[PDB]
Length: 128
Ligand SMILES: C[C@H](C[C@@H]1CC[C@@H](O)[C@H](O)[C@H]1O)[C@@H]1CC[C@@H](C)/C=C/CC/C=C/C(=O)[C@H](C)[C@@H]2CC[C@@H](C)[C@@](O)(O2)C(=O)C(=O)N2CCCC[C@H]2C(=O)O1
Image (tube, rainbow, N blue to C red):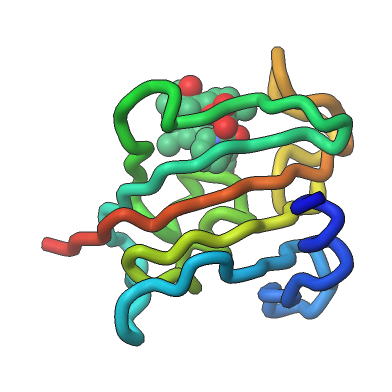
């Protein structure tokens, strides 16, 4: 399925080249511009654990998830991955625990040492 495919066929987008964050572009976005550090980014996403269980979805809330890029407001894999996206892009990210919640996990849903799968749609990004 999709998690296996990004694991085996994804692009390492880490600066360290440690395969901690792998990406596949699923729907190509607009033009060439990607968000910059500090931009307000609007996304939709769903997340799955490696046991197949969905742990979250913004779609189910009928509102986007909003954060400021590159500020550690989200897990490292998201700051790294969303920074590579074009407006309108949909991607798959595979996030090893060192770029996610590590040994701590995130109670109640995310166990220790969890590799996470996300589908992310970059809806918009704005500075100012
Ligand atoms: C929980 C996490 C905490 C954050 C991690 C980085 C670290 O440097 C920060 O100190 C720490 O606060 C952060 C919240 C997003 C920041 C921006 C939100 C904080 C407000 C408090 C409530 C947040 C939520 O309910 C999240 C939507 C919820 C929390 C539990 C997670 C397992 C999850 O369901 O989100 C989830 O899907 C997830 O894993 N997220 C949300 C989407 C972005 C990626 C990821 C995430 O980084 O969420």
